Every structure is written in structure tokens, then in C-alpha cells.
Image (cartoon, rainbow, N blue to C red):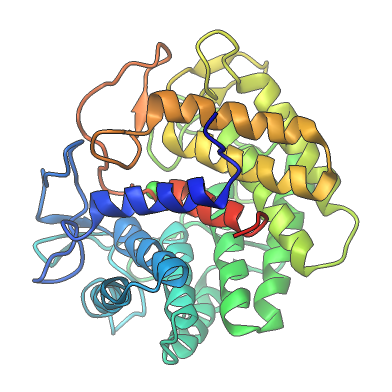
Amino acid sequence: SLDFRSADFLRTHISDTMAFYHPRCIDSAGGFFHYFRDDGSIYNATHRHLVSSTRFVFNYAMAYLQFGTAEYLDAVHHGLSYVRDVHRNPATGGYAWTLCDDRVEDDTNHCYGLAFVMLAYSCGLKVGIKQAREWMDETWCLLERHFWDAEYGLYKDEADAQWNFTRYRGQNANMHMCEAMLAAYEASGEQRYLERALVLADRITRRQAAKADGLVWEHYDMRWEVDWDYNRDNPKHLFRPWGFQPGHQTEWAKLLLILDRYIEVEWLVPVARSLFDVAVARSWDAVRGGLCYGFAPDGTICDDDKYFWVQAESLAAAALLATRSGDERYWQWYDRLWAYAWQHMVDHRYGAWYRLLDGDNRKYNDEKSPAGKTDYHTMGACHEVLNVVWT
Ligand SMILES: [Cl-]
């Protein structure tokens, strides 16, 4: 009976998750704490990760835009200071990947990191920080100088502190960069950002997908040919897992439908539908509920864990596909994804979502939000659905 498609539900859910993190995530000494137990207690106060530092700026910016709460605007400023004063290396323009007690632990320059930095700065401009328009331009320049490969229409992934790149090429940083470029466009109105987002979408969801039977594989060589073996022996790596990730197929479907809002071009929706339909067919657990984490190129599930962000990205995609297409089967997907998530993944005692469950929907431990997780994916999905329903 709960109406998962109502603004009432979505706004309340976002506010429940904000109540988990706020104000306990704020470190008055600098930035945010990045490791939280189920009950909100901090289990590692000293280790910090660029992906959390940036995602928490998104959390609070999108919440301020929705609710107007002054404490949330203050937290956007606090979070951006940490990104600019502690992560950022003024000598190179790069950003520390991880810190331990404000000392740089890993200074590797990850494109994935810069996507999140671009997103945090775009959020800063959206909340009225006019200086963020320049920080966005500085980040664009840094990306063009080192990461962009015009010949392929895609960014390289990973360089050391002197900008020496590895040969690895990855869809995931490009996917988040498409997302960041859309945010940058929404914040600044600059056409270059929207157009770069479109180029990235075309190259990944059409050209690269063609090499893997119509779905987006994660890992590639330096010539952007598929690397079928990368991390086969470390398949649960956090950013570079092995196998097709249904969550990334649906996340792309969402990004293509956001592009379709701003760009008039025929190919976006049919590609979005192909990615979403195949991904959920292959990965939905019809017995226990929920989308599984990974499947191999033969279709066989290779990781049946149920992750928070997979469900979230998929319901956001389903809502966008439903509204654009008028196909009610997409709202049925939306409803079943939420029914699963509400029953198993959302913590009704403390708020926010569990990170993952095993295939039997059991908890592994009490580490709700380790470094990298801020419920940016779950609140972000709700903010996105709020763009297509009456509020
Ligand atoms: Cl997250």
C-alpha cells in the first residue's frame, strides 16, 4: 500500500537517510568521517577517501536544493574546503585518493576521483558558490591536459603523481564522468559539458557495447578492446569487479534518459531500453528478490550478493524509462525493486541502506557505510525520480 512513486515517499526517504548521517558525519577538524556502523557510530575516524569526501558534498547539496536547510548549505562549504585544502595538491593539480590523519596515503591520480571532484564542484555552483564555476574549468583543463584521449573519445583511467599512465582502460570512470558532465551542464549551462557527456555515452553504450554482445563490459586494453581477464582473480575489487555489472547497465540507461531530456537525438532511448531489459532479465532473483551483482559472458551469475547501489540505480532507470516510454512494465519494475529494497535493504531502525546482503538476503556484518558509501546512490536515485513525478 506504500506509494513508492509518490513525492511524499521519496522526500521522506531522503530525509530519513539524511537523519542517519547528519550531523554525526561532520568532522569539525576537517571534512567528514567516512566509516559508519549500522547504528551510526564511527569505526575509523582517521582514514579518508576522495570518493566519500566528494559524495558527501553531493548528499548535502542535493538535500539543500530539496529542503533549504541552512545546516546543509554549511556542510557543502565544509566539504568543499576539505576537497580543496586537504585532498588537492597545489603543485600538480591532482587529488589525494586516500588520506590518513590529513597525510597523503595514496597519491594515485584516478580519473574515477576526478569525475567525483567535477560532480562535487558542479553541486557547489548549483547551491550558489560562484567560484565553483572556475574550479570546474580548472578540473576540465586538468582532464584535457592529462586524461582525455581524443582519438578514442574517452578518458584514460589511472596515472601516478608525475602523470605516468597505466595501460588499463575502464568504462566506470567514463560512466561517472558522463554523470559529472551532465551535472556540470545543469549547473553552468556550458554546452561543452553536455556535448562531452554525449560523446562518452556514445562511445561506451554503442561502440564499446558492440564488442561485448550489446552490454557494457568494465575492462579494456589500451586500444579499447575488451580485457576479459582483468581482476578475474580479484573479482570483488570495489571499483573494478569482474563480470558484467547489471547495476552499470541500468545506471547507463538512466544517464541516457537524462541526456534525452537535454539533447534531441533518436538513439538514446532504444539503447537505454536494450541495456535495462537485458540487465534485469539476466540478474533479477525471481526466487529471493533483488538484482544480483554480476554475471559472466555466458549469462551465468558469478556474484549473487545484493548490493544497495544496484537496486537504487535500477529503480531510477525504471522510473525514467516508464515516464519517457509510457510502458507500464517499467513502473512494475520500479515497484518490485522498491518492494525488495524496502523489505531487505533499507534500515528501518537507524535509516540509510545496508551496503550488501548475501544471495539469501542475510547481512555480512554491521559495516553499513565504509569509505566510498555515503548513500549518494540511494538518495541520488530518489532525487532523480523526483524530476519526473509531481512534487
Ligand atoms: Cl553511495
